[PDB]
Amino acid sequence: QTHYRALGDGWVEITALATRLVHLNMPKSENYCRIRVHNTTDTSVKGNM
Amino acid sequence: GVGVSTGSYDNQTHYRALGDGWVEITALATRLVHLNMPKSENYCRIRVHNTTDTSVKGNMAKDDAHEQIWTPWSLVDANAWGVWLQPSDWQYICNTMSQLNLVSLDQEIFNVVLKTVTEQDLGGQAIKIYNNDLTACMMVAVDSNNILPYTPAANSMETLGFYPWKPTIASPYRYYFCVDRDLSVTYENQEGTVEHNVMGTPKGMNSQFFTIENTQQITLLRTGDEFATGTYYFDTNPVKLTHTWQTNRQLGQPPLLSTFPEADTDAGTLTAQGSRHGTTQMGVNWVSEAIRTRPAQVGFCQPHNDFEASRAGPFAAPKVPADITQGVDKEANGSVRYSYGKQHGENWASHGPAPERYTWDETSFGSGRDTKDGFIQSAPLVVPPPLNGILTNANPIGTKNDIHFSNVFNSYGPLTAFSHPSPVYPQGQIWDKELDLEHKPRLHITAPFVCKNNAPGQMLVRLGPNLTDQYDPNGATLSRIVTYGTFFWKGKLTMRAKLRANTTWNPVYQVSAEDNGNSYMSVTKWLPTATGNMQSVPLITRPVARNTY
Amino acid sequence: GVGVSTGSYDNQTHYRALGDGWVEITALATRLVHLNMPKSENYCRIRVHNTTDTSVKGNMAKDDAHEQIWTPWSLVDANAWGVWLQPSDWQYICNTMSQLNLVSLDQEIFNVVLKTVTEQDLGGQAIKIYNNDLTACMMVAVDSNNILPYTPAANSMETLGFYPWKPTIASPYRYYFCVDRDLSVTYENQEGTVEHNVMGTPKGMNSQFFTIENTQQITLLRTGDEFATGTYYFDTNPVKLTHTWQTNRQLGQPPLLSTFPEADTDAGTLTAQGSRHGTTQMGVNWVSEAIRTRPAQVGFCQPHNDFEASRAGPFAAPKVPADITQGVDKEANGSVRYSYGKQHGENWASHGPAPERYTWDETSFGSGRDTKDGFIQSAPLVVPPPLNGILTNANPIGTKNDIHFSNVFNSYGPLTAFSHPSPVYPQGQIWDKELDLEHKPRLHITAPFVCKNNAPGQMLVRLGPNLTDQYDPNGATLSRIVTYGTFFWKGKLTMRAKLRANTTWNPVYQVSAEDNGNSYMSVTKWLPTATGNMQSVPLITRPVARNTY
Amino acid sequence: NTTWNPVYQVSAEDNGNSYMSVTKWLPTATGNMQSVPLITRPVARNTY
Amino acid sequence: LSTFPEADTDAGTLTAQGSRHGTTQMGVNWVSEAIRTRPAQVGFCQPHN
Amino acid sequence: PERYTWDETSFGSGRDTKDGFIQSAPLVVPPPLNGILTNANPIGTKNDIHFSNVFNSYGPLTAFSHPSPVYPQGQIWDKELDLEHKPRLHITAPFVCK
Amino acid sequence: HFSNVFNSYGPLTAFSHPSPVYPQGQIWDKELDLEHKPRLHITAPFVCK
Amino acid sequence: DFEASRAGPFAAPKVPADITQGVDKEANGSVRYSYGKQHGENWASHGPA
């Protein structure tokens, strides 16, 4: 629920609440990996900076 | 003294949020009222009898024959919504608040000025000179006990002006005398003559001639004097700033769907009617949405344009305002037709003498009645009914084929629950006085805030008589030096409102001001033109929908 | 009462030395303001569209098409330096003090007089008679919360008069309406047509029509009443009454001289560049005064006469005022061109309708930019550069040979440290209101004292409406007895200054008044002529130089 | 509220080709919700 | 405004530019709405892409 | 995906690029052909690039408005960049945590 | 070229303070006596306030 | 950029930043120090440079 509370000389205290069901799947690998992205198919074409 | 001022111009509206979601609106209104001298210094019993209308056969609705006592006093009547609030204030209140209630009313008269006119030649063509009368006064009486008849000037569209920067005038006070009027009902070019078009003599039993001198406490005000009538505390009921949509076929639990739609286009079929649970009041062995038992009727049917007649002439019986349906007809549900002037909202660029009119369609969408699609079946329900088993809005009642059963059908009953009609912006009426009868109405369609205990005392002003040196009291001459006056009126209307609560997922309706175009809410209506011609068209009072049940 | 006065004329300036070298200047200003009745009693949205200028191709700078809401209220606007101080006071403050700061502002309205005019023949040719209205009032509202738009009358040269012995007038109040204006850029007698010269309708999103009746607390003032708005305490930053001279080639330690001059005529050679110590940012193996590393840039380059356009039409972007260099051009550094009238400093013997104009050349000699002598070399420094390795103020940008690189080059950066522009005497502007945006400007070029918290509330006066006996509110006639009024305005501006310190050996620059001649500071300008024709030309604000770094 | 005229407001319009029709913020027959952005600053204010 | 409009359609002409009071930063002997001196720039130009 | 261009509602800070122009240093209106630079003249030699593509006029007297928060697919807060001279604003979030 | 004239200092520009230089550096500096100071001095990292 | 305001042409100071893979040092304002034997020059340098 969101709760509006008018407190003082024209000041409202909005109290936003958010509850979700997060679905945590297992990781792809258990290692910290330094992956490199290099799209040569785009940047090899002249004019694609 | 004559050279010092006795008040302050104030026109601001002050919102004050106090407590758990309650705002205290403090509307202020100051005008410059222009009091002219009365037409005569006598109380006169004038009679209106339009024989040119009612002599024509078929004009019983065009009757306005009556008698009125015309007093020399003028009315400072301020119960209209446009006096106190600007259109931005009304838009913010109707969008942001959920209900409105009246609290109190202070009123004041200050900065009195009386001036007499004289003539000079200066070119051979005489001009007026407006001198100053430092000793002439004006008479003020507040009818706080309501001895005099309650005549609201919002009935005649004659209240204070709605634009604060323009000087306004005071409406003349007059009330109704009780004489008998009889008019014979006849239609258009009917063979025969009008039997009754008479009006009676004053009756000895019920004749009330009130004077304002014998009934009130009159304060004289010179140029240095002020008047202030104190805080009248209202005892009204709150009106709701949210509108309803649920009809009698949208109350309770919906029937559970047997099948569900696969795509976003098709519908979902319910349980078949012959094998469906629920309750009805008909004797058939099936339940349907039309004949399911509801808690209460939301809107009632009311007779269209019934002209009753009881010792005063034919008058149309008032209808409770409800929504106009998909069947667009506005007369059946009683949409009020306002006719106002340049002081109260007409565009000032209208050179014609015709007023500005507006039909107020009500936003109570569950109480509206569709007259062409209403029907009555026989006492045992056998659908599809035969020809002689159903009465629709095509069959003639009596012998008249222009009149159907919806014109005479009243279905107000014990389980009828309708909504209070919305306040109308600027050319509305704020409060009313409860009728002095033992069994009161449930509502007034002229005002949303009917005062339970006492109406606020209506203010009566006039100019004191300025006499010449020649004055014979037994001679009907009354030379009477031509005077007039201007004074300042300041009033404070306190209101209490509650803030709106947001429960729905979707964005709800709001009154937003649109761009310049053919739309109803273009900004160029609420902005002055090149010559400063302002205009006030009404605003929606109830934008946000609410749940009935 | 009507026969007693309610204030005192006061115009003196009181210097009070308090503390360790701090003077409390107490400037006082009293004028007789002449309030005439408004042209109309309506708020009107007037539109200006000079098609005779903008229809000619090449006249985008001559555009002044807009819309304004014209209020019936007049503005008592006092923020100009000539209102409070005489020229001797300004000369003493600018010579003797080192900085100036604003403290507080009291304002007052007293000795109200309202008079109505009438006609008499007396010779067959009618003359006016100015009677007295002891009961008519005038309306005063101070916008201390700044609801209304901030329109300084120092923009239109319409503030109070600068000569205390002459009666002055109040400027009419009006503000800007937000409509869209589009103008197509084209040069002189270009083949083709002007594609865009349109102006739009009012927009529903951003339209603000303010009335002064619904927003303010209006005090009515008769002949015996006074008004006094209390001490507004300023929260500004001090301006400095000393000027700077150090450019970017005069910051830090000078290079030590290898040889010294024998006589008083010859110069002293420094250490040779290839074998000189120091730091640079170029890659060359020598240090010089041009390429030596400085702490910060003192003046920045700014684009000359850039006409931007965003939903209102072409407007020139404002420049920070800096010194005009040995390269005398005044447009590049933004020397403000003032155009004022006889009430504000024009010689009264000028029978022509043309105003008195004056270019204010700034005295910030280190921040000035020389545009003909500016140049850009290639990224590795190789001096002397070839033709294709240098961009000077002769090369065409784009294809236009009338436009060079200095017209588009902006070099405002993080290490840019410029000086605040000096206040301008009499026809200046003292304070301003900070723009209601999240990221404010660092300075305002219209006023040296931008109020941090709230601007002082602008004072709005008008005459109360005097009506004849004939007044129809639904008829647009408004007969309106011809009245006017005069009142007295007294204000007190408190300032705090610091005394100057003398560190230099040589006599420093001072603003002295010279004898009668062709000089700019002859005394005969500040003295009345045989018929009493005074004149106020501006004075130098910052005579005494100071050290930047 | 200082201005005389009615100021701009974000109102939800009827089913049509408008940007603020209610049928975007209502689920369909199979429950397919949708969130398009809303205007953050409807009400104009005075800069200077 | 030097002149005011009579009807609701026409505009109102201001004081002529060569004989108008005010302040500018250009060297011309006339004041106009385009070249009038303002307190601050509201929007800045920024390099496209 | 679903795409949407967020047009800002700061109507005083907007720049009209076709109607922007630069005149020469002494103002002589109507200017000649070589005395005005409009949004039609080629900068460098490129006729697809005009002077508005390179013109930056951010200065000391520049006062713009903070960009509005975007509903649902906005971003509420951000982290201030760990540099000595911070930006005046973040265009990704209206509430930069101090 | 265009890089010789292009200034892109703007409101959303966040750069780093220049590092002190060993031995032949400069420790402190004096702030310039102007109303609108620079954000930094490139001669010294510690500008005395 | 060699600006000029009442004292002669002076180069405008740049904020020092990194020289990129595009090795040019003049664009980002790399400071060029020139010092002597008292401040860090090798004392075996017989030249006056």
Image (spheres, coloured by chain):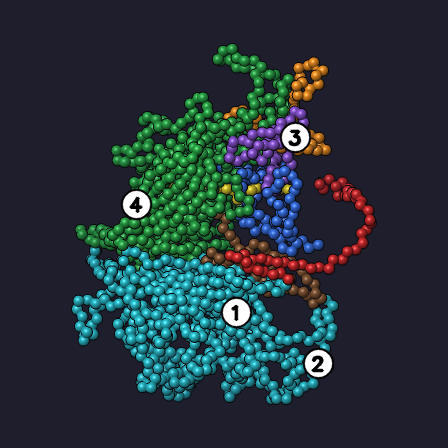
Chain colours: A red, B cyan, C green, D brown, E yellow, F blue, G purple, H orange
Callout 3 touching callout 4 (CB < 8 Å): no
Circle 1: residue type: Lys
Q: What element carries label 1?
A: strand
Q: Name the residue under label 2.
A: B277
In the rendered structure, the residue with mark 3 lies on which chain? G
Callout 4 touching callout 2 (CB < 8 Å): no
Which residue sits at x=35%, y=76%?
B147
Residues at discs 2 and 1 both on one chain: yes
In the rendered structure, the residue with mark 4 lies on which chain? C
Query: Alpha carbon of mark 1 to alpha carbon of mark 3: how far?
Result: 70 Å
Circle 2: residue type: His
Q: Mark 1 points at which residue?
A: B240
Q: Is mark 2 on a helix, strand or loop?
A: loop
Callout 2 touching callout 3 (CB < 8 Å): no
Q: Name the residue under label 4.
A: C8
Which residue sits at x=66%, y=32%?
G19
Which residue sits at x=37%, y=39%?
C27
Residues at discs 1 and 3 both on one chain: no
Say which mark, if any, is on residue E45. none
Q: Which label lies toward us, 2 or 3?
A: 3
Q: What element carries label 3?
A: loop
